[PDB]
Image (cartoon, helix red, strand yellow):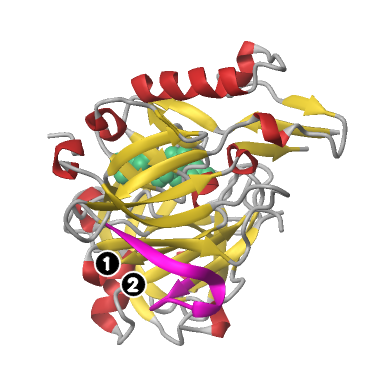
Amino acid sequence: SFVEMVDNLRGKSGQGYYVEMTVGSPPQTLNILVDTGSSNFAVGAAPHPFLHRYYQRQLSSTYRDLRKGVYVPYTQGKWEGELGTDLVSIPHGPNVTVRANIAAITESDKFFINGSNWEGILGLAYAEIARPDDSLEPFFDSLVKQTHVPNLFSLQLCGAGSVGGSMIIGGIDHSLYTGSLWYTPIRREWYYEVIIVRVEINGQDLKMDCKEYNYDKSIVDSGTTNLRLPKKVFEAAVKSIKAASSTEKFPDGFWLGEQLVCWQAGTTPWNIFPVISLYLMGEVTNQSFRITILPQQYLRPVEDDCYKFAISQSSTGTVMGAVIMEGFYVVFDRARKRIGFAVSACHVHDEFRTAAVEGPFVTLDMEDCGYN
Ligand SMILES: CC(=O)N[C@@H](Cc1cc(F)cc(F)c1)[C@H](O)CNC1(c2cc(CC(C)(C)C)cs2)CC1
């Protein structure tokens, strides 16, 4: 649901995906990063070395001040600014205009990125995690309350098939995937929180208490680049990934996500890097499904062929970031408290292996896999 939004995303590797928006009357055009890992809609509203444009409130006939300040601290970066409401629309989007909350960003630190082409962020997760508090209605919530747009969006993030993709607001576009959608419950409405019931690398169960995979949570987050795994899980995965690829040897800064590794163009040894299967809780009792990630997703290319290890240690739970979401079509079915995965039409290539969404699997005591 529908052709107008196909290919409405762009970006640079490791700097997120953005969609074109306009705010104010007359309309001012900004590129906005699409972030299911937070819930604030915020935009450059003042000069910055890295911004090529920004939101000019005084130039907008429709702007209203909320006379209240705001700040948001992300994993690394943070911004603060001023709350208002203005009229907002997505040009390659549904055909509508909403009055939404906007944080006019006045100061920032390590937020905007030099390469960038985006001037703001669209937090698509739920009011619970919004700043300054849950009474600040998120953008998707206002678009739903104010229009007829169904309460569902879908993200097809593609990986260089200078990245691109689609954000279908309001529905599912059957032209963007193959095979069946498989759905996992949204465990609680705050982040897009899910439960991982099993983990296998090259078909070997990690054999951990399934609570460790969700410790203290597992989320789907398009605003975080890497797959981020709890310490105990990170250690076990890097252990098997090391051993699968031991034929060759790598700097330590490589496994820590720091320094790139290189091979002669067209000779990257993909076969020595294992596939990772994440099993998600399903819709029916004792039933789950798996997504399989290929090394082409977790060895993210940096500009010979050169890559960073795109899995990292977490102390805040599992993060399924952009590299996991790439080559899947991921449906955020808020209306039904579920997230659907299918093989995307921009799926990642290997000459001998494929990324897959497969089910059904039987898995006992999936309830026990949730932390607390
Ligand atoms: C890398 C990163 O941090 N990405 C930002 C998006 C981003 C992209 C970018 F290019 C630059 C940034 F500074 C931020 C994304 O929201 C991360 N989502 C999560 C967190 C959100 C928050 C804020 C709350 C929800 C507590 C208010 C803290 S961790 C769950 C992990």
Q: Quadrant of the N terminus?
A: bottom left
Name the residue type under label 2: Leu
**Sequence-wise, which precedes: disc 1 or disc 2?**
2
Q: Secondary structure at mark 2?
A: loop
**Which residue corresponds to mark 2?**
152
Q: CA distance from mark 1 to mark 2?
A: 5 Å
Which residue is found at the position 33% from the left and 82% from the top?
149
Q: Position of residue 116 (x, y in %)?
A: 65, 49
Q: Which residues are magenta?
A: 168-184
Can residue 72 be seen from the camera position used here?
no
- How many numbered tags mark residues here? 2
The residue lying toward the viewer, choosing from 312 and 87, is 312
Q: Is residue 92 above or below residue 193?
A: below
Q: Quadrant of the C terminus?
A: top left
- In reply to whether residue 86 is colored magenta, the answer given is no
The residue lying toward the viewer, choosing from 2 and 89, is 2
Q: Position of residue 314 (x, y in %)?
A: 39, 27
Residue 358: mark in rendering: none
- In reply to whether residue 173 is colored magenta, the answer given is yes
Name the residue type under label 1: Arg
Which residue is found at the position 82% from the left and 28% from the top?
263
Which residue is found at the position 23% from the left and 78% from the top?
145
Which image quarter has ligand 1?
A: top left
The residue lying toward the viewer, choosing from 143 and 57, is 143
Which residue is found at the position 30% from the left and 87% from the top?
148
The residue lying toward the viewer, choosing from 117 and 340, is 340
**Which residue corresponds to mark 1?**
334
